Image (spheres, coloured by chain):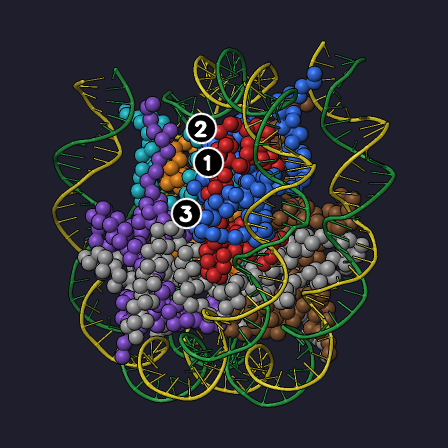
Chain colours: A orange, B red, E purple, F brown, G blue, H cyan, I yellow, J green
Amino acid sequence: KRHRKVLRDNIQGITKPAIRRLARRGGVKRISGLIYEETRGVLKVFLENVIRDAVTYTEHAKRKTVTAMDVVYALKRQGRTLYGFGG
Amino acid sequence: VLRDNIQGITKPAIRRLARRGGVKRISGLIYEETRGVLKVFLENVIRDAVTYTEHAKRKTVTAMDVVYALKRQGRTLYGFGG
Amino acid sequence: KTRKESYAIYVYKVLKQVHPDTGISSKAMSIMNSFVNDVFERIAGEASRLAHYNKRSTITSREIQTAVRLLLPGELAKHAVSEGTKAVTKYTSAK
Amino acid sequence: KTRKESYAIYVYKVLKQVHPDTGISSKAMSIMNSFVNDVFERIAGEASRLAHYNKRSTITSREIQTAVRLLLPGELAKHAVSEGTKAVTKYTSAK
Amino acid sequence: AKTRSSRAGLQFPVGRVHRLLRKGNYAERVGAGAPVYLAAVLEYLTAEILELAGNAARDNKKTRIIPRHLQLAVRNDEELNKLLGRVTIAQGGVLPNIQSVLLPKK
Amino acid sequence: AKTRSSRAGLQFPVGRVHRLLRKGNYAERVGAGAPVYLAAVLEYLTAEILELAGNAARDNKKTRIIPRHLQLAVRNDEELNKLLGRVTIAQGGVLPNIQSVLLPKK
Amino acid sequence: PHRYRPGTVALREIRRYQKSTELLIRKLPFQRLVREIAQDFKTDLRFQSSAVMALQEASEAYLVGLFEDTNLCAIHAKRVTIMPKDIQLARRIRGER
Amino acid sequence: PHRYRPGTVALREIRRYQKSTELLIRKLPFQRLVREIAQDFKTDLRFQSSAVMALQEASEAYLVGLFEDTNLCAIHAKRVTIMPKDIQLARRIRGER
DNA sequence: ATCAATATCCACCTGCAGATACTACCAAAAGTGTATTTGGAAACTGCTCCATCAAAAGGCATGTTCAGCTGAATCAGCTGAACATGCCTTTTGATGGAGCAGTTTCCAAATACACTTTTGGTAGTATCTGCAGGTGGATATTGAT
DNA sequence: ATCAATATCCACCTGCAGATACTACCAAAAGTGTATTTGGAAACTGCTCCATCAAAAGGCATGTTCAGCTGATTCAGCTGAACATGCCTTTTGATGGAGCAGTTTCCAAATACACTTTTGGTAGTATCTGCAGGTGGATATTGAT
Ligand SMILES: [Mg+2]
């Protein structure tokens, strides 16, 4: 490794059109201008909660790699069971 | 003067519950609606409680049958054992 | 060389029984595997609790039976109870 | 005739430290007992899963710790962890 | 030399199920009919989902069930929908469903 | 003859907790410190609630804690409220709270 | 002949009932409804007194909270009067529907 | 030139996206967000690519279902436009806030 | 109604990523017969649970009357959809290097298990007392004028 | 503004429901001494995960234009709040009566244990085939007029 990259503001990588698509799938016809920042914030909380639990499982196992299983168990704890990734 | 048991859950009692829930004004249709919801609530919980009773080979539903039923229904109750 | 079990071959047999000329993608199979594991733990979990509640130390087919009635909705519960009872009965007389 | 075990005495002792001239109603005690039992079950159940996930046969204080971190909210987790490690330290260095 | 599966009339592996019940520490003892009953329940459930899923495959002119087919099966069926009310099927999408008022004209 | 609770400096029964852990089928084996740790955590949380519950009795001109005080303690504290977010404390009632739009026009 | 404005007594009852903890449905009618419903699952059933009580506590806590959400839904539609559609919306978002 | 009326294309997009199952957020930006959030919890983490994919499937399924609930809240208010107050009401009734 | 721009449809073609096809250990089923242990079974006995009715205790049903809320109608200001244009960012498919999972085999530290002494915790039973509920009188809120 | 009706607040009093306190067992703690069982520690080999760079492949960003939605305003009609009068159901509490949980003690069936043999299910390597994605031309939907 020559260096290591600094991650900042990646929430803006969740673009207005991507958010619009998700709304569309959710059956939404018309979208107020403020929705995009609100959704970004809601997604950030969602990810924080799940990643925190996933990472806790990673650490408990003394690993440095977050496995699909860490995420699946994290998701399960939070009443958001996922099928298709090993549990 | 017959009148089904559900109707025993009276307008004023439903009114009182609403009040504890901070409700100021209540449409006349709410009373029937509420009775319906309470019935579905009681069905789901009682069913599971009785399933516990039957399993224990009893003819009496215990507090614990109910407590366990509420737990598994995501409605944990404190103060009645367990 | 690392070993990993799944219910896939069983899911595939059952698939072959109900839709003889129908296949299944590996991702669909992965979901089917998840589903079985998921329902396995829920039934076994309920059975576990049920035993404890009654100061039993054994999980018998009667615990699984009650767990199924607790866990599954109405019509699925009814039919799963048949198939379970049926299988147990056959297993007893077959031996 | 049978003995009915309860956390009530310990709850009562802890009440005395925290509020020496405060008592407690029957029902309020019952609630406190439920609360201890519930939290017991949640912590243990999570610790149990941790061991299973990691192919271990033992529930050590490490599982309890991780379990607490998973279950308790931020600041409550922090203090609980310190109280736990404290208790384990005092107990180990005990001749 | 007979499997307990074939003894019970089951495609699902009873030996396996007995074993997993042991390792899961659900109780001290596991009765002999427990894994037989559970394997039958598991098999019943997967047959029910596979049936409806295969039908969804067919309604979409396909030979191979994919996750979307499993999702259509589950979500279109009241009881499977509830059983899996709090589960996400990766790559399942959603049911086509547009609310009335959102449609044009009067 | 000295108790593990006194050794660990605890009011809560380390002995009982160890037992309850074994007879809970949570795992094949239970390490020595686990019940110590667990017991501490239970004691801690109890003291947290009893503290705030005591305070609540105090504010209401009372010396005996009733369910109401436990309710006020729990639901007025963000963290306890979340921990107990899906729990019902019998005879607790609710926090006084009226939505401001329902207030008469001052 | 003094008369209180519509909603004044309502507000008063909110304060009164939010202050207390008594159960708000009469015990007996609740008991009948419990037993009636139980009867369809198993006949000739008996109930511990505390079992009925547990059921009432849980039911009333359930319904009170549902009225809070219901109320929020009515306020969302810029009303102050709860309606069935408010209950229906609350239950749908809760995943009860 | 030809122009569709406001809402026509929107309804088209609803049918299209409700028909398909691919992820609607871009693979890499979502990856960055995961790594950033995680890094703030713990430095020097790696991710199995399928851990990231599992998070994406979970995240998109949460968001699509939140928008259905949100949409229901807008329509409750007799609107066809979702607003932050709609998301907030959904999340409150869901017990998320 | 017609007329035309643009989206959608269904059906067929085709190579290829992702299925299904044949194969050879081995972890895990099955079998077989000692040895333990559970939990129905049966017979109890004693709390609670149902019923009654007696008491009082009290809350709820019904009718009238009007305040003020909800919903319809109307409208302007302006947000948010559609779409044109220009270009960055993600996607995809290389490669290579290290960083870390994951498999295996050692024993030292730790937990089980069994058995014997020594409590702490519980049920029974006997005292003590917070406070629910009532009373009186002072003043606050609300609503009319 | 005043004037009054009624709700609300505080202080003080009191008996008893529901606390705390004191006691005599004993099931389950802790003690003591072998009997297994575990999951780091070191030492492998060996992938996936990360990083980069180039080309390819598409989606994103921004400005413009105006359709039609949101939210403010105003209004009238109806419906739900308030409250009087008026009846009947619930609460209370012996009674006491009996049922059925919960207590104890039994043993026979079923479960754990252990070993030795026999699979079935998995990982490795090598052909088959649904269908994604492209294209074609036929037809549907939308919106102008
Ligand atoms: Mg950072």
The numbered mark 3 sits on a residue in which chain? H
Residue on which the image places disc 1: G88
Q: Nearer the viewer, residue J84 or A79?
A: J84
**Residue drawn at the location 65% of the way across and 36% of the way down:** G17
> Can residue A40 be seen in the rendering of this structure?
no
Of the residues shown, which amino acid type is indicated by label 3?
Ala
Residue on which the image places disc 2: H79
> Disc 1 to disc 2, how far (Cα)?
18 Å
Judged from the image, the secondary structure of the residue bearing numbered disc 3 is helix
Judged from the image, the secondary structure of the residue bearing numbered disc 2 is loop
What's the mark number on residue H76?
none
> Disc 2 to disc 3, how far (Cα)?
24 Å
Of the residues shown, which amino acid type is indicated by label 2?
Arg
Rendering coords of residue E13 (x, y %)? 32, 69
**Residue drawn at the location 48% of the way across and 34% of the way down:** B2
Q: Nearer the viewer, residue H26 or G20?
A: G20
Quarter of the image with the C terminus of chain G is top left
What's the mark number on residue H61?
3
Q: Ligand 1 closer than 8 Å to the CB at disc 3? A: no
